[PDB]
Image 1 (cartoon, rainbow, N blue to C red):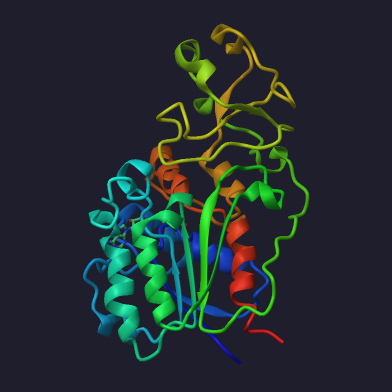
Image 2 (cartoon, rainbow, N blue to C red):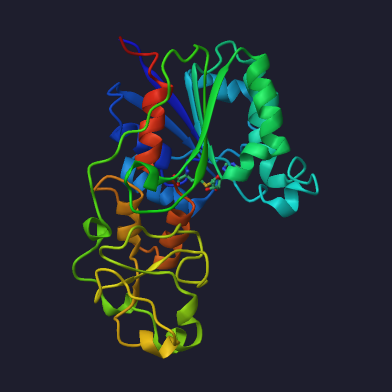
Length: 320
Ligand SMILES: Nc1ncnc2c1ncn2[C@@H]1O[C@H](CSCC[C@H](N)C(=O)O)[C@@H](O)[C@H]1O
């Protein structure tokens, strides 16, 4: 009977939508994605066969938003403004990349005839401490919202990937039940690997000899993979782990040259896509898009696995 109509702000490649669709909420829903990134939109449209609204969220009018007649807000705002450097200088609140998310809560939400009955926000841990969210929290509270938040990682529910993120769950009804995480069907890094990767993905020997020791290396059996970020395969450190197909448990070495013969390679875009929990039919392999472009979008996406469970909680007032 009841329906879920979502405005997918900062839709990107449709991580928030994917999360909902794979969850057990099982209420048919509609999605209206907003994003100015042409490449990201192309992937979204390719997979969801729906057009992305490119209206800039910095200045979008209340009227246009309300014309959508939606009752749900999904969003993962730009995360750049939220590091210790910017935040310790109190510059996050004035950061132009935060202008869109402040606009939505300052200028839109408090004036809607029908406030969204459910709101889901995803961002980096430091967002929780930002002046931006501090204000958003106050606004939500003043507008009669109940708010539950959590900082967690996919590994917490048995997914072999470290991506610690901050999640905000807001709605107009109080939460009767304690939030709960369930362990996902057991899986290893093995389960996400493509089985015939082109050699164009293996780490060049010259790169190995110069920065090989900086890589976080994993085998098909190792505990987890590191957080995949935008610049994966471009910048060595902190952008994601690489894979060794020779050892179930990568055994560390002392010299870079010792890595030369372990057939090291980057994870493919399709592999990251599977690790982030997108549907088997979902693909960033849009015609014309290079691996870099796909890596960038994927690096900026989400863990559909985690969000699926948190959304089921957010919407637990729609059952029984
Ligand atoms: N003023 C603005 N209007 C619309 N989108 C914006 C924007 N400023 C930044 N963005 C978008 O917000 C997105 C943040 S990344 C989030 C991606 C999404 N969660 C996914 O699963 O892929 C970026 O793609 C960026 O294009």
